[PDB]
Length: 156
Length: 156
Ligand SMILES: [Cl-]
Ligand SMILES: [Cl-]
Image 1 (spheres, rainbow over the protein chains, first blue to last red):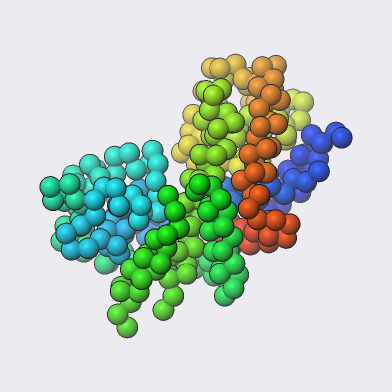
Image 2: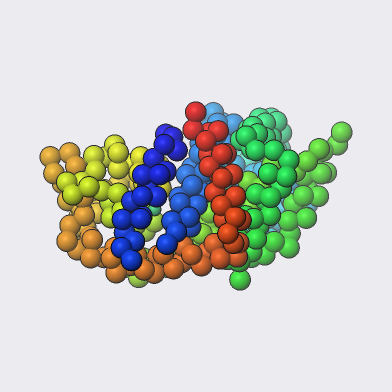
């Protein structure tokens, strides 16, 4: 794929405007494609291990944010990046791989669940870094501020 | 949800750093949550009509970018915002609702498929605008530039 047809989409929206900007529609298109792009790149570090995005997200969330006893399914969702129909069965699934366990509830990593994340984490941190490499200091800070500001507007 | 635990996640990553920035990980988290937020807001204009995101995207793509005969399944994906397992059966599904049709192939809207988009479009353009309202000129332009630049880095 390329960004060679961005002007084609822009002019396509102009035709629709008989009687004045396509910025919003193009920005959301780009954000949508960015998400998919980021998705393919991030999964590379955990695909080989048989995990999908939703599974990975839960495990890493436990790894960085779960206290020794674990996180209540509520606070667990509040601390995870992904939330939605994608995580409709992530818990049950992970329990079945013995990567997490219960404590009634309360979820937390099992010795292997943690072993896996420890081994993958270096590769995740790398991809995470690489993926944002094209930008740079302050560019990444501003992106952070805007996404936060936009996201803040919708979280009301 | 709120952005009240962003510092908690940041400090959580710091603990992991025994021996130096969490920006990348927090920026991608924010981008991930932004996508879900945007997803819930955009669907409001088409949910009542029984369409999901993948169905809507195809229809709108045809509406703005399909010439009179239609788009070849290839160029159709190149002009659509969404691409992935979500659109694994969007075509077959839409044919079944009689919103699109064939031309052997080649896809295009049917009289109603177009009627629907015409009726929804005003509401979509509104949400699309609203959702980016919190920012402003140049803020939306810069967001566009960065997402494009990042996205450009991954589309290689
Ligand atoms: Cl679009
Ligand atoms: Cl994370």
